Structure formats: C-alpha cells, structure tokens
C-alpha cells in the first residue's frame, strides 16, 4: 500500500469491546483502508478464533494489536485524540464529522501519532474517557436511527482517513 | 428523517446474498443513513434489529432486470477493469450523482455476492461502476461495509443540499 507510511501513525483504539467478532470486523475495516495500528483497551475477552475469523485477510492487524489495561496507555505519545460522541449542549466539546476527522488526522499524522478512539458496543465512551479527547466525532445520521454499529463507525471513519490521504496524492 | 423523501428513490439492490446476517447488517447500515428501499435479487434463502422494517418491506425479485426497471441511473460495485472497461465513479461522486438523480427518478445501487461480486453480464446492466478506493494489498470490503460506505456518501451528498 502506498499509504502504509502516511497512515501507520493513526491508531484505532477500541475501548472495552464486548464482542470479539467486532474486533475482527474492525481489523478488516481498517486494513481495507490502509490502517494497520489497532489498540484494545481492557477488552472483555482477548481476541479469539471468532475475532480472527471476522478479520479474514486482516488477521495480522489482530495479531499485531496492542492490548493495554488503560486508555491513558493507548493515548501516550499522541498529539491528537478524537473520540466518537454526539454533540453536547451542556458540556460542549469541539466537533468533527468523519470527513473533517479524516482531513485533520492525516494532516497531524504527517508529524506525530493520532488516536481515533471508539467506545463500547451500545454504551460508547464514558465521560471520563471523552474528556481525554481533543475533539469528538459525530457521524450525521437518520435522526430516527442514529447509532452506527461499532465496526461500521470504524469503517466510515477509516474510509474518510483514506480519502483525506488520497487527496494529498 | 428529513432525508426520507429525497432518498426514497434510491434502491439498494443485493444480488444473491448468501448470508442472512449480512442482509440484517445491510438493513441497519441503510437505515442509519436514511435509505429504506431494499431489493433482494434471488437471495440464496429468504430473510429469516431496529431496521427490521427495511427487511420486512424488501422487494424480493428473481431477476436483476426487475430491480433495475424504471431506474434512470444504475451504479454497480466493481473495481476498474482493463479488459471490460466501464465508466468509473468513486463513492463520493456516486453519492452526488445518486442524490441529484433521485430527486426526480429511481436510482439503483447494486452490490454483488459475498467475496466474488457481480458477473460481467450483471455489470453490463449498469451505467457506471463504483470502486471504493482501498489498500491494494487488501481491497475487498465486507458486503455490509461496502453498503455502509456508499450509503454514507449518499447521506453526505443529501446533507449538502441543506
């Protein structure tokens, strides 16, 4: 991949993933867009045969994953941290959409490591975790049905990171 | 739900889907982006979360032609081909063209089989092919993920009309 070096600095950080299959689907979503650096923070169960199975040709991304107990460890060394969250009117945070997150991530990663942080199936990220992010990224969606599956959220965000990369080419 | 009428003319057409779970995930991907209009072309088996309505209301047809009937724009997922060259779109341009055409007439966005995609004869029924730019070492997205990307670009194009 001619994107390998530009994108190897961009970490995809999954916080306390409940279903190991989702770890695998994430690894595949990542690798198809050229992202290869996966960090798992305190996963309920470590990657297993199901995670390897859903990773398909991206089982190397699972294999090479960093597994750490705390979020701080996954963020150490990163200059730019973006977490998935809807906007808040009462504890406002600076907001990105996937497209702007892609642009910003690629611009930053030319210099220094970036973390794109995703939370737990259903529950998401906690307030304590969200407060360690520089920006929150929200995916504009059907107001009737507005929550994407974990791996689908990663697939969108990774897609926009490759698109931003491609623009630099 | 303000997108519902601008996007109801966009058909998501799955050809010979072999995994009923993919059918579900596609429905979810669609619905989160406002797409509701699902067409299943000879699914291996008939359909067996919160987007169950998209599955219940699906149009189950035996031929691709039926799923394409009435459509002024048909886009199918494929890589570019050197030997069967076809006019190519990326997801972003596909989303712009789809939303523009859908204000007025039906559009079909066609996804092939797991792993192997669409036949050349199926591909020749499309006006454009859409290639999702990807890692050349590993370029094949899961069916539901391909739908998710294409549906996301469709909503982004719709949002730009607001």
Image (spheres, coloured by chain):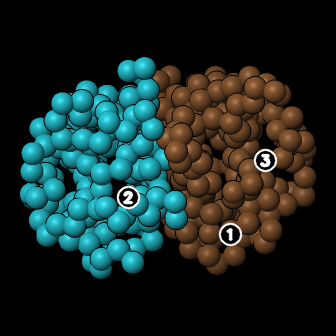
Chain colours: A brown, B cyan
- The picture places residue B64, in percent across and down from the top left corner, at 14, 60
- Residue that appears at 30% across and 79% down: B45
Q: Residues within 10 Å of mark 2 (few under 14, many from 20)?
A: many
- Residue at label 1? A20
Numbered disc 3: what chain? A
Q: Is residue B55 left or right of A66 when viewed as pictured?
A: left
CA distance for labels 3 and 1:
18 Å
Label 1 near label 3: C-beta < 8 Å?
no
In this rendering, the label closer to the viewer, 3 or 2? 2
Say which of marks 3 and 1 sits in front. Answer: 3
| Alpha carbon distance from label 3 to label 2 | 29 Å
Q: Identify the residue at horizontal 55%, vertical 69% (top origin).
A: A54
Residue B70: where, in percent of width, then height? 9, 45
Would you say residue B59 is visible in this rendering?
A: yes
| Mark 2, residue position | B54
What residue appears at the point 56 percent right and 44 percent down from the top-left corner?
A: A146
Name which quarter of the figure residue A105 lies in.
top right
Query: Which residue corresponds to mark 3?
Result: A125
């Amino acid at each position: 991949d001619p994107a390998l070096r530009a994108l190897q600095n961009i970490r995809i950080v999954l916080v306390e993933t409940s279903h190991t299959g989702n770890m695998g689907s994430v690894a595949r979503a990542m690798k198809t867009m050229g992202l290869t650096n996966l960090w798992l923070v305190n996963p309920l169960v470590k990657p297993d045969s199901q995670a390897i199975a859903l990773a398909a040709g991206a089982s190397d991304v699972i294999g090479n994953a960093h597994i750490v107990d705390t979020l701080d460890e996954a963020l150490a060394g990163c200059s730019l941290v973006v977490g998935t969250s809807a906007r808040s009117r009462t504890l406002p945070w600076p907001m990105l959409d996937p497209r702007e997150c892609g642009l910003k991530s690629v611009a930053e990663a030319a210099n220094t490591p970036v973390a794109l942080v995703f939370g737990r199936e259903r529950v998401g990220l906690t307030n304590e975790e969200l407060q360690k992010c520089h920006y929150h990224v929200a995916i504009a969606a059907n107001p009737e049905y507005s929550s994407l599956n974990l791996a689908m959220a990663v697939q969108v965000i990774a897609y926009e990171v490759r698109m931003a990369w491609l623009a630099t080419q």
